[PDB]
Image 1 (cartoon, rainbow over the protein chains, first blue to last red):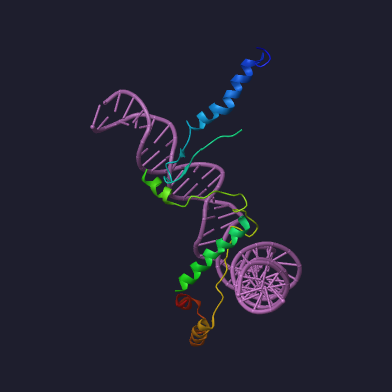
Image 2 (tube, each protein chain N blue to C red):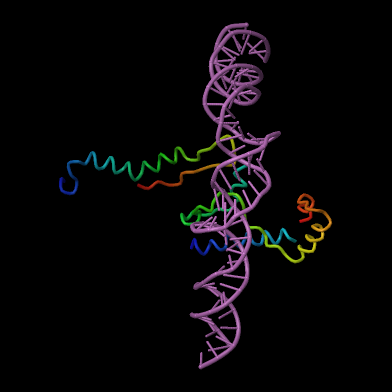
Length: 50
Length: 84
DNA sequence: CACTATTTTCGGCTACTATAAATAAATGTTTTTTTCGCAATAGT
DNA sequence: ACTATTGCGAAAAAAACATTTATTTATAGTAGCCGAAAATAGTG
């Protein structure tokens, strides 16, 4: 058990899930910044890489 | 790729001169040209964002309409600007 | 092997800030402040 | 809803004050756009 699946399971596997999956889930919740002045202007967050 | 495309940029600006010689807001934003940015293309130097441009070099056909109004009046830039 | 066409290769040119130092009526804006309007909010 | 009391918001404006309008020298330095020419490479 401890060989393939260590003793710092909790801090490795939680942070490594944050890097891959959840970082895409944040910019998809705050995509498409917009302004009221110049209404035909937009900027969009398409992806995230660390 | 950026250096060879630079010559194409001024190529459209030559044909503009000789032709002169002769929700709803996002719909047209989709109709605009979509392009990828390569950092070498937009590059700026000292020759950027400054007064002046390249004047069209003059012709002999322009000389005869120049020298005749130059001869009638003393020196009047005003009306000859509308002539050309 | 040799023509024809082209992509360099090389100036050529044309402009163009500068500089000061006048003149000057605009001719911009800035901060600083003050004015004036509207909406902000809540109680009519 | 609508009217009044509120705060800020925007804009004047004031005073200053540097920023524009046309000259002339060049001189060296960029920088853009244009052929001018010259070699080179595809292809006949």
